[PDB]
Amino acid sequence: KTINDLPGISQTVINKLIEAGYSSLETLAVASPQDLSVAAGIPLSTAQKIIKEARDALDIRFKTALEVKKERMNVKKISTGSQALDGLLAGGIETRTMTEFFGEFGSGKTQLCHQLSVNVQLPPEKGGLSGKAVYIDTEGTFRWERIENMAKALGLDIDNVMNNIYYIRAINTDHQIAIVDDLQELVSKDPSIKLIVVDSVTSHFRAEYPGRENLAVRQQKLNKHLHQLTRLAEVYDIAVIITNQVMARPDMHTLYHVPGIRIQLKKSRGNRRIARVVDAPHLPEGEVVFALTEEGIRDAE
Amino acid sequence: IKTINDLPGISQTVINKLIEAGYSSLETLAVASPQDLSVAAGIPLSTAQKIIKEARDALDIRFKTALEVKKERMNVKKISTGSQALDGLLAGGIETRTMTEFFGEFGSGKTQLCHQLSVNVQLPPEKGGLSGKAVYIDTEGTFRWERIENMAKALGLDIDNVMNNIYYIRAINTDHQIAIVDDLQELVSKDPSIKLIVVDSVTSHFRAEYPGRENLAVRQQKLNKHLHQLTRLAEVYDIAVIITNQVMHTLYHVPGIRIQLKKSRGNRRIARVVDAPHLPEGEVVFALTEEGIRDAE
Image (tube, rainbow over all chains, first blue to last red; front, top):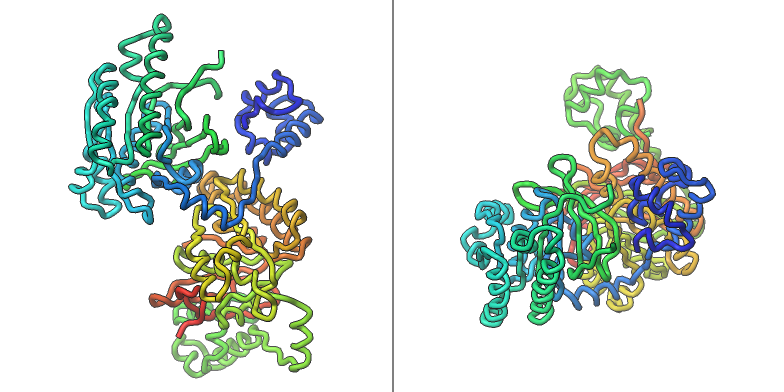
């Protein structure tokens, strides 16, 4: 994974490679040595080396049909709505794990949450888990209308869909924490819930513990909260999603992160959005494209 | 030659009067009565008898001996589609050493075809196969292990054996698709049993990552490079390569054979030869049953 982990590679060129738009290995693997040597200012011989080393690094494993079928019955995921995105996520949002989508405002984190709170209700055959979703609204982002249109586009009972989503406003950090604490009860008292969504987790934490003077305690507290969510997910076999708003994490000191899977979302040509894996145990790196339509999260074009 | 536009000594004004009359295909004109064509299209009777002679020759009807054909059948092995009709259109079935494309609207039956072929390949020459394995590169998550199963049962095969004879892989985008094909050479070498490679929805990612007419150029350049790659493997390791595309003074096409698929009344589907060296123009009809690809009736 990652370019930083390439064998026999100086740490000076690794910069001239990210400073040239080559962030992922798949990008290097299929790139031309001649074109990489110019766009990055690297010795032609060094180019054919970084690409030879990048080409091996690719985890191309051809699994049998049979084996993959065993893997499908051994796991169940909630489909995002965009075939592209689903593939990046090896199938969809997995239960038992916490998934984070972080990105600038309008990168599509909010759309995605609503989309998942509905798709989750669909039967396995149609991409869901015939389950309920709990939507913890941190900064008043829930839109009953988005739920509606997404609902229609699937020809579902608007009213039924909405009734399958538990809603709650967490006004502050303490409340957020206590709400997720109470989450255990509700999930025990109603085993149908299979998706918890916490939109803008970090938010109150950033407001109640601002700046670099608190960062220590903020994360100390933030992380504790997320450990919590994780455990819940793992223990009651339910999918947990968190969205975190940022403005640009170095790309276009190594910090610590709790979240199992971490996908970054970027804005593109108006209607389009790019999704890229940044942290994930079994997911392979590489970004893909999708879009925001009225039907909800779909693939582009 | 295919398409009416390729007819020799034919004006371009009538070519419109013919298509405006309903004569779009050549076999339809070949079997047409010059009198009725003359009226239906408002074309000189002399000119009607001419276009139908041209069209009927365009068909390329060769009468080989029974002996000569038998020789030609041992000189080549093909994977059968399941539908006698289609096989017939394909001169016997899917040929190795060649890339075949099936394109058409969604549900036109390109997906079912790919699954059908990934199973028929494992069959022994006597039963239509080549006793080989298949590699299914899934572009948009279309693989259904369920379809492979029923297709499997209907043949009285070992579901779990068949499935174990199909390598699967998910190509989440262009770069991955490309890379997966680059490594394809190793795998075929590493395992000479593999005789079928199927790439469902090739064009797909390319149309996503390089959208519109603004990229078309780079799309085809990359697309052709990709495909030039697939061909070589087919040719070099003596194996069939199938690709499906989803559609609804240059134009740069690589694919050897290009069969178009169309949706008909419910269960029925039509397949028409669009591009092909040795294959004769003409469409045929088949059907998507639960057993898999079969003939309609």
